[PDB]
Image (cartoon, rainbow over all chains, first blue to last red):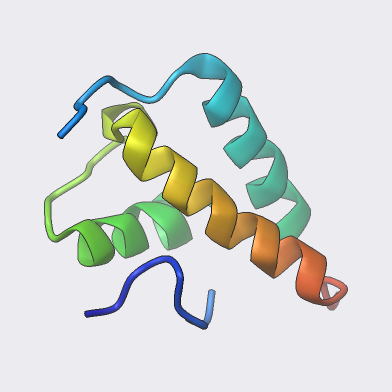
Amino acid sequence: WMDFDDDIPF
Amino acid sequence: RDITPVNDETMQEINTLLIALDKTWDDDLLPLCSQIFRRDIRASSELTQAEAVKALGFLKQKAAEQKVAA
C-alpha cells in the first residue's frame, strides 16, 4: 500500500 | 490503536511545513491522508496524533530534500 514512508509526490 | 486526537503542538509543526512547501490541507494533505489511511478525513483536526506524526515525518522529508521552486 501507499504509506507516508514512501517516496510519494506532493 | 491509540485514537487520541492530534494535539495543537503537532498541528502547528505541520502547518509550518505546509506553508514552507506552499501546500495546503484542502488541496494536498487532507486528500493524501484520506488515501493513505483509507478513511474520509474532512478536516485537519480529525487526524489522530499517531496519524499526524506519520504525516509530519513525510513533510519533514519533503522540506529537507530540496529547495521549494518558485
